[PDB]
Amino acid sequence: MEQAPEDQGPQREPYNDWTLELLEELKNEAVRHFPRIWLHSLGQHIYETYGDTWTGVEALIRILQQLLFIHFRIGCRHSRIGIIQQRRTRNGASKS
């Protein structure tokens, strides 16, 4: 906290005028990058949907698959550590 509405000058949080500087840095980068800008979007595009017709749609599905795989892994991690966690996973005679 500080005795200021958000910014003042002396009293200054790790945002405030830093944020402008951060936006100014973003502008500096972005404008320098402006006569180039290809790879930036090219990479993103191809990754996302390259053909966009059961070619890039397949790529997009691959991103989904990757995601699903991670979630599956996490689920499995939080299962095999306690198979018989009062028969957590082996839900046969579901009591304990």
Image: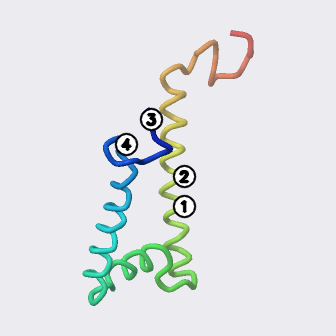
Q: Which of 73 and 27 is in front in this view?
A: 27
Q: What residue type is labelled 2?
A: Leu
What residue do we see at 31% from left, 85% from top?
34
User: What mark, if any, has residue 3 been given in the picture?
Assistant: 3
Residue named by callout 4: 13
Quadrant in which the C terminus appears:
top right
Q: Residue furthest bottom?
A: 35
Q: Determine crowd level at label 1: few under 14, some 14-19, many 20+ residues with C-alpha closer than 10 A.
A: few
What residue do we see at 47% from left, 46% from top?
6
Cβ–Cβ below 8 Å for labels 4 and 2? no
Mark whose residue sits in front, 3 or 2: 3
Q: Distance between the residues labelled 1 and 3?
A: 48 Å
Mark whose residue sits in front, 4 or 2: 4
Q: Determine crowd level at label 2: few under 14, some 14-19, many 20+ residues with C-alpha closer than 10 A.
A: few
Q: How far apart are marks 1 and 4 (CA)?
A: 40 Å
User: What mark, if any, has residue 93 been given in the picture?
Assistant: none
Q: What residue type is labelled 4?
A: Glu
Residue named by callout 1: 64
